[PDB]
Amino acid sequence: SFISTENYHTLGCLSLVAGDLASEVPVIIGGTGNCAFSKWEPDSSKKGMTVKNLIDAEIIKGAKKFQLIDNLLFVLDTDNVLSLWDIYTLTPVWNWPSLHVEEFLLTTEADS
Amino acid sequence: SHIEELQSEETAISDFSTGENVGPLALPVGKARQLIGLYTMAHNPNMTHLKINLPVTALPPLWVRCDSSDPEGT
């Protein structure tokens, strides 16, 4: 089933991340265009995902890469700037504008 | 704040008010997030502060009104 982001991401979607929090499936897609962020969640009454949250391309024009460890959406913007976000409501928690991080990797001895 | 200089004898269908005033309103959710972030940053010891060289003093909470302009319902 193809779901089109042509009505929200007019310049192509750049990064996609999928998780399972709050008894849902938050699929956060970061791209450039009318809306920088699109949060798709599966509709329980239908067959497909619908948009639940939208962030305009005003402060951040888009997301290049995501990494969702747990309740922490580390968002790398189009300016190679890393930031810390809370996935529950997408509120600004932290920002890292001093470090021009082209790519960031988070590694830990994961047990649970 | 303008002077009428055209004559319109046609019938216009519109409604008008005779004493209604807009009271307190709510800020946009995107605007509210910026202020919530500013409050969070102003009271964070891990900020590279530009005007304060001391640990930040705690203050009673901030609550920004939201107009629910997003499908959050907030």
Image: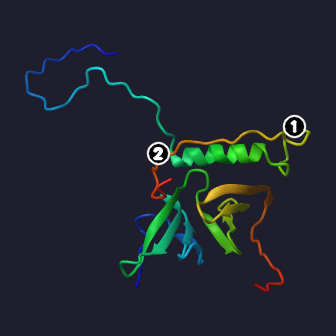
Determine if residue A9 is in view. Answer: no
> From what the image shows, is residue A93 above or below residue A15?
above
Q: Residue furthest front?
A: B60
What residue sits right under mark 1 in the picture? B52
Whole-percent x, y for residue A58 in the image:
56, 51
**Residue type pointed to by label 1:** Ile
A56 left or right of A111 in image = left
Nearer the observer: mark 1 or 2; the answer is 2
Q: CA distance from mark 1 to mark 2?
A: 33 Å
Look at the numbered disc 2 and give the secondary structure of its residue.
loop
Residue situated in front as seen by the camera: A51 or A80:
A51
Can residue B19 be seen in this snapshot?
yes
Estimate the x, y position of residue B32 in percent, counting from the top left: 58, 45
Does dot 1 land on a helix, a strand or a loop?
A: loop
Q: Chain of mark 1?
A: B
Q: Which residue is mark 2?
A: B67
A23, above or below B67, in the image? below
| Residue at x 21%, y 14% (from the top left corner) | B5
- On whether disc 1 and disc 2 are found on a single subunit, the reply is yes
The percent position of residue A29, horizontal first and vertical second, equals 55, 70
At x 45% / y 67%, what residue is drawn? Answer: A51
Disc 2 residue crowd, few under 14, some 14–19, many 20+, Cα 10 Å: few
Give the chain letter at badge 2.
B
Which image quarter is the C terminus of chain A in? bottom right
State the image coordinates of residue A103 (x, y, percent, origin top left). Answer: 75, 71
Quadrant in the rendering for residue A8: bottom left
- Closer to the chain start, of discs 1 and 2, is 1
The answer to whether A61 appears left or right of A80 in the picture is left
Q: Which mark is residue B73?
A: none
Residue A62 is drawn in which quadrant? bottom right
